[PDB]
Image (spheres, rainbow over the protein chains, first blue to last red):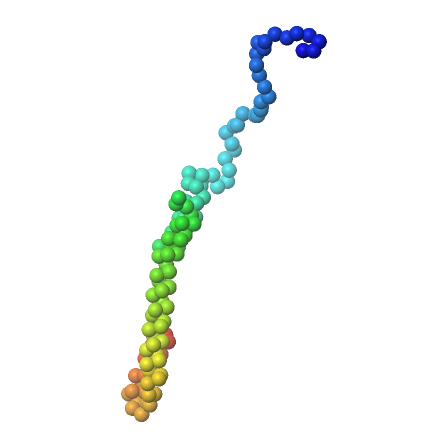
Length: 51
Length: 62
């Protein structure tokens, strides 16, 4: 701008983050526990013990 | 809010009543043992000696 003259921006932008699209993750061993949180499983174990 | 630790505390609270019951039973049995001990331990009667011995053995087994 010190040596030329600009116009008002015709397109405003900024820095941003590019990532690879999340894919269907390869199922993990012990993915059969995913429907319930770990805390539920531990409470189940200790309720079994207590009962 | 409800969590794993709170459930552990609830279960331990329920199970500590059992420990209270056990210790109360202990002290009652030992009070009976003291009533037998501090009381005269004469075993002149064979039947009385046998009864006292079997009571002691039963309480020990319990």
